[PDB]
Image: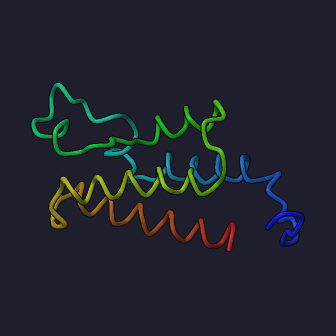
Amino acid sequence: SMSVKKPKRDDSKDLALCSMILTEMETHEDAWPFLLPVNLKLVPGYKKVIKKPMDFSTIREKLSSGQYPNLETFALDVRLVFDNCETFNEDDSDIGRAGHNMRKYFEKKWTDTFK
């Protein structure tokens, strides 16, 4: 509360560390469905159904331009990518499986880096 603060967590490396995680997600062999924005002209149903599209290239640009106020807003957009994928793709599809795999890969790196 006013003039009453928990001890200051060092957040000075968060930007660099989020960037390194994102590099590791970008280079994973199952990243291909997620690298670029879904083409809303060419994929029927996507525009109407997926209210907030997100992809790695869009996260990279937001990261690089100071549009994440903290590491939690960064994680929310990564998770959005996988939540969208689950909304639109059957579990038993290449893309469906890719999204489960990448979500797992992310959550481990997140816990190991920050928790």
What quarter of the picture does the C terminus occupy? bottom right
Pick whichever, 75 or 35, lies toward us. Answer: 75
- Residue at 37%, 35% (x, y): give it: 36
Q: Quadrant of residue 97?
A: bottom left
Number of on-image labels: 0
Q: Is residue 13 above or below residue 112?
A: above
Question: Where residue 103 sits: x, y (%)?
Answer: 42, 64
Is residue 97 toward the left or the right of residue 25 in the image?
left
Q: Where is 86 relative to 45, above or below? A: below
Q: Out of 79 and 93, give the one closest to the viewer.
A: 79
Left or right of 44? Residue 113 is right
Of the pair 65 and 92, the residue shown nearer to us: 65
Residue at coordinates 89% horizontally, 64% vertically from top-left? 3
Judge whether 2 appears above or below 22 on screen.
Answer: below
On the image, which quarter does residue 79 sit in?
Answer: bottom left
Residue 114, image x, y percentages: 69, 68
Q: Residue 89, position in %: x, y?
A: 18, 56
Q: Is residue 17 left or right of residue 105?
A: right
Please state, as top left, top right, bottom left or bottom right, where the N terminus lies in the image: bottom right
Which color scheme did the rendering employ for the protein? rainbow
- Extreme residue in the left direction: 44
Image quadrant assignment for residue 2:
bottom right
User: Could you tell me residue 93's position as x and y percent?
Assistant: 16, 60
Name of the residue lying farthest toward the top: 41
Asked if 100 appears above or below 14 in the picture, the reply is below
Identity of the residue drawn at 56% across and 35% down: 62
Question: Residue at coordinates 56% horizontally, 52% vertically from top-left?
Answer: 73
